Image (cartoon, rainbow, N blue to C red):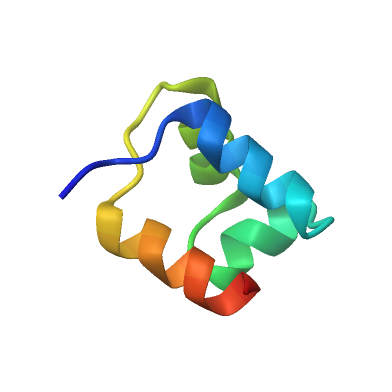
Length: 57
């Protein structure tokens, strides 16, 4: 399963007008974790990526 690119994560969050905190809450994660995902510091678990897409579309 492919992890999303950081730019894809940011684009998907911006598409639904969510703050980083709101996105993190949607996937039961911390704000710092979402920031690390968008910075490329950590890879986003593909299941959490799927959850985010399911809950925002």
